[PDB]
Length: 309
Length: 112
Ligand SMILES: NC(=O)c1ccc[n+]([C@@H]2O[C@H](COP(=O)([O-])OP(=O)(O)OC[C@H]3O[C@@H](n4cnc5c(N)ncnc54)[C@H](OP(=O)(O)O)[C@@H]3O)[C@@H](O)[C@H]2O)c1
Image (cartoon, rainbow over all chains, first blue to last red; front, side, top):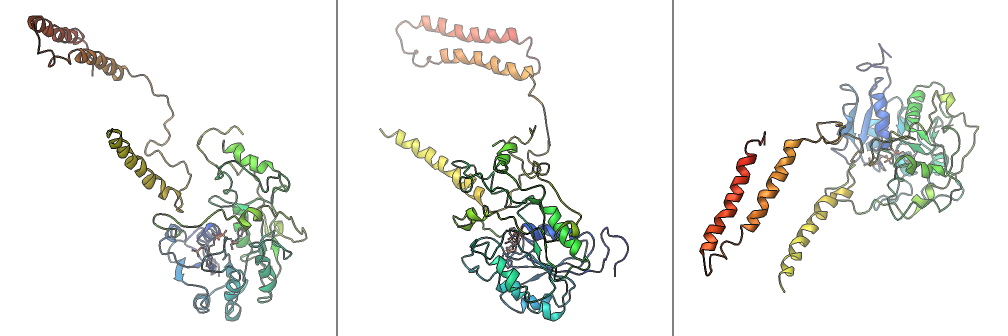
């Protein structure tokens, strides 16, 4: 039962759990539950020290850590047993040399769609992507739209989410560009045609969840995440050079964490804007954020002073 | 022919060792945020380097005392001669031509 005011050292009655919640997105959600009060049980896989930069997030005795693997059907059953809502951001980019990547969007999101359904969670949540279509594309972009089909079977109430290409602070989406000091900028594939997608700013997505986190009355009913206006140009790849003025890694280096001459180059140009009929955002709002104004901040390079844009 | 073998040997250990230190973890997968937090403990510092003179003269002031102690250098080869008086009478001139050039300026060093 919610008490007092939402500042910090308050209650607001919701527990949570957030799986993943180390890399770019998950760190940036929990930080919005280390404010309005919660009990955020964040588990994590292998990382003892990479999770510390998080801890001054909840006040005291709010967030609490566990250890888990995720192919063991117990590790997801020991935590969640006490919970209210549980969202899931889990999953990543390139196929691992260990995890074969095929069912890590299939078996894992179900492996946590195991006893969670049984044990009496509620308002369970999962992530989708605006561009994933079960027609043939794209080797990574596929297997994600399987979860929308395969996993939706379980837990009839989901409110599974469908956002666009997002640009954060430390994000890897718009940052693959401007790291491209290289033989030259070569668009994908050397064509200025279908760029760009709906680049929503990471705050609005992470303010969507906690707006649906007790919504109320969105369960089973999936939503998709509007971008700003409107579609976009080739200039986005020029815009990068317009202003820029031209976890658990290792001790020394990582052997392979590449640019992936594979799905990566073709995942960025898949565009496929899709169905409007999803509610999907202002209803869950109120948020929408532009690009032109918010792209200076995340972009700071070797002038570090001049802008005049 | 073995000198250059003893020089480009030396740099090539040094010009190697920059990359195996600077560069090797430089491409490591850690965070390395671009934030303009760098340039320690004088956070912003927007100015030109102003002309400050008594910094300057201590350049010039040396450069001239420098020359003649190249002129002064071939004494110990010249100590072997025929008529030597033209040495001692002459050798001792340069020095006193050096030491004079002090005494004048010595009225004003300023804060050096
Ligand atoms: N909605 C979108 O716009 C969008 C865009 C790009 C990608 N995605 C996908 O939607 C989710 C957003 O992820 P993100 O933005 O937070 O980036 P992310 O770097 O993939 O974050 C995932 C975190 O969970 C970890 N992880 C990877 N595989 C795991 C597994 N089987 N089990 C447990 N943890 C695993 C990752 O490394 P650790 O195991 O060390 O924790 C990382 O810590 C991901 O699934 C991503 O593939 C979505």
